[PDB]
Image (tube, coloured by chain):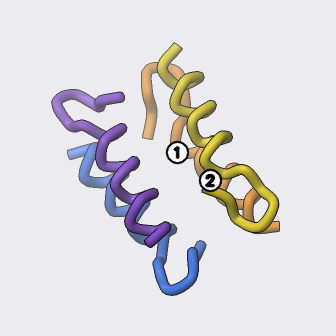
Chain colours: A orange, B yellow, C purple, D blue
């Protein structure tokens, strides 16, 4: 799930975890 | 849009901006 | 915020609203 | 990744796929 060079998939997974402490 | 005291809405909006840069 | 002709931004905003109902 | 009864994780995964046809 990439937007050009950005790995949106990865950043979103990190956010989900960060918000579910 | 928060999960507990985590500002998920905001962080997601920041990801959409970064991904779009 | 689109992936090709898919309006991802919009659909995501709709998910945030539904999840918050 | 739940918001009350809503499975945000699941809906978001479906959206990612839908936008990556």
Return the residue nearer the eye: A10 or D2: D2
Counting from the top left corner in percent of width and height, residue C1 is at 36, 28
Instruction: Tell me the subunit letter for badge 2.
Output: A
Neighbour tally class for label 2: few under 14, some 14-19, many 20 plus, Cα within 10 Å: few
Q: What element carries label 1?
A: helix
Judge whether D16 appears above or below C5 on screen: below
Residue at position x 38%, y 59% in the image: C15
- Alpha-carbon span between mark 1 and mark 2: 6 Å
Q: Which residue is drawn at 49% across and 67% down?
A: C20
Residues at marks 1 and 2 on the same chain: yes
Image coordinates of residue C13 in percent, x first then y, are 39, 48
Residue D19 appears left or right of B15: left
Identify the residue at horizontal 31%, vertical 42% (top origin): C10
Quarter of the rendering containing residue C3: top left
* Quadrant in which residue A16 is drawn: bottom right
State yes or no: discs 1 and 2 in contact (Cβ < 8 Å): yes
* Label 2 residue SS: helix
Residue found farthest to the left? C5
Q: Which mark, by number, is residue A13? A: 2
Query: Is residue A17 left or right of C11 when viewed as pictured?
Result: right
Q: Is residue D14 left or right of residue D9?
A: left
Q: Quadrant location of the N terminus of chain B?
A: bottom right
Q: Looking at the picture, tell me which residue is in the foreground, D4 or A20.
A: D4
Nearest the camera: D21 or A15? A15
Mark 1 neighbour class, 10 Å CA radius: few under 14, some 14 to 19, many 20 or more: few
Residue lying at 22% horizontally and 28% vertically, measured from the top left: C4
Q: Name the residue under label 1.
A: A9
Q: Position of residue C2 (x, y in %)?
A: 29, 30
Estimate the x, y position of residue B16 in percent, counting from the top left: 52, 31
User: Residue under mark 1: which chain is it in?
Assistant: A
């Amino acid at each position: 799930y990439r937007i050009x060079s950005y790995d949106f998939x990865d950043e979103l997974m990190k956010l989900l975890r960060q918000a579910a402490g």
